[PDB]
Length: 170
Ligand SMILES: O=C(O)C[C@@H](Cc1ccccc1)C(=O)SCC(=O)c1ccccc1
Ligand SMILES: [Zn+2]
Image (cartoon, rainbow, N blue to C red; front, side, top):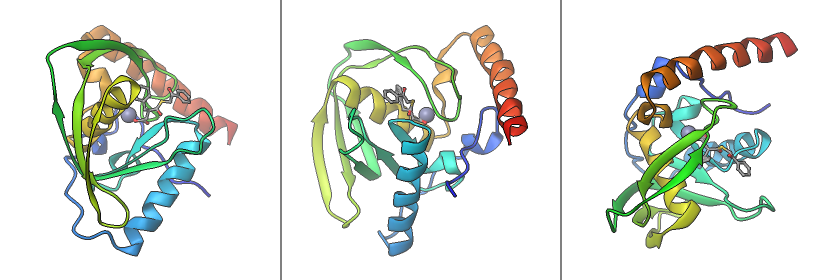
């Protein structure tokens, strides 16, 4: 029913994504499938890389109500400061694993929407954390890449256990 989400340490999460050529109806369908996949997990962000579609497409909904969807296509993210903010990040590609990452606390985001319109907004708080995390997917990076290698290894062993249990539950 929903799109399959790749799991760390799958090497395909390391693929650097290509920009989207045109916002065709097939990329519109992929976005809507991504949203369903993301809302089901549940999560608040998903990059197309995570469903094994190596294109510069991110879906996101930061709302409690699951009713403020956002799309970023071909995004450029630029820090507006060297101040970082800590945040406890998770990731549907590192299921049930959470730890602290310090990222620039304010960023400019420029991207296009599902109608092919360009936009530029500035973000802080949870938006800046999540857009940087999702941009990182697009460049083949996971939030575990910023943890010590014993946190990484333990994350990996734990995730392989979770994935096996999820297969078994099937
Ligand atoms: O790459 C991902 O799969 C998305 C990820 C986004 C994210 C979470 C936390 C920090 C930074 C980025 C997640 O969706 S995890 C979901 C989550 O933590 C959450 C879900 C519902 C309400 C509140 C938080
Ligand atoms: Zn992620």
